[PDB]
Amino acid sequence: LADADAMHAKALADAKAESEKVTEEAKQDSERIAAQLSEQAGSEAERIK
Amino acid sequence: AEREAMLAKTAADNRKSAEQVAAAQADYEKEMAEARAQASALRDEARAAGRSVVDEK
Image 1 (cartoon, rainbow over the protein chains, first blue to last red):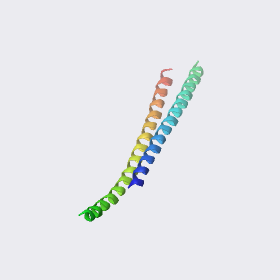
Image 2: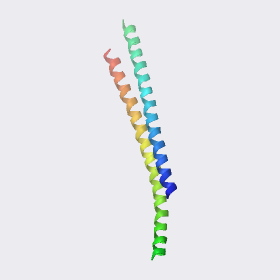
Image 3: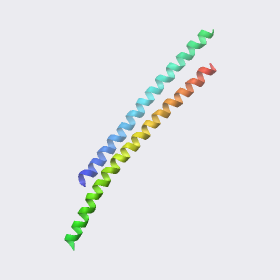
Image 4: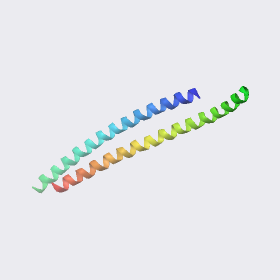
């Protein structure tokens, strides 16, 4: 039971760490997607010009 | 009485250890799914905003 509680705590800590890491990775992915979408929009605008 | 209490509490603690580890991976999977869904929402909203921006431009 003591080991199970300790493993619960350790797994919860690793879980929150993984959640934060994936959130940061998703934020970076969203930044890249927004940047490339804006660049593509600029390319489309100049093509229309 | 103390021995019977020891036996009953030991059985209850084995059951509780099993249930606690079970809830451990249950909550781990639940929060991992929540984080992945939040990341998907981030990506989707970013894509929608970019689509709106490019359409307006």
